[PDB]
Length: 125
Image 1 (cartoon, rainbow, N blue to C red):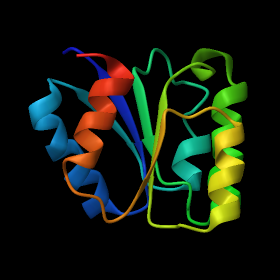
Image 2 (image 1 turned 45 degrees about the horizontal axis):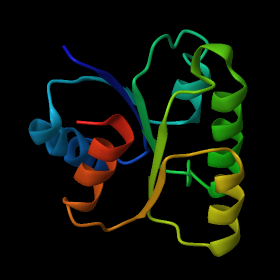
Image 3 (image 1 turned 30 degrees about the horizontal axis):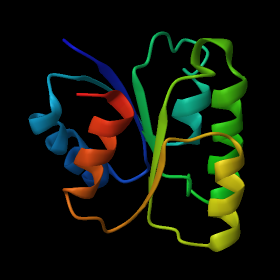
Image 4 (image 1 turned 30 degrees about the vertical axis):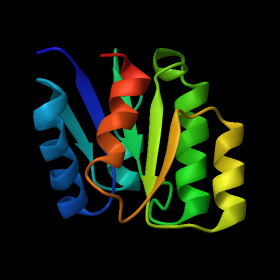
């Protein structure tokens, strides 16, 4: 068990696709958050998350951004590295997302190679 990852994404198939990519990265624990309700219902319980991968469109950018902020202003997760992988490519929402600090911004679809490197860089390897 060399890592716990938090997947914030409404789409189950995207989450499954993401866990798979981790078969090459390493042996990781996954905590899935399928919607707003699930996030707020547990983010105050989050402890020692090695990596957060989320879709800012949660379900819409304004909600994802709020979640992002909550994550950054939450003590136990303020520095936790966040990788944004999203289907939305609105320029302003992306730009706004970068103001909170995130390790990467990936657009969907993305070659299952794009995410792999990102994780490896962001996490060292």
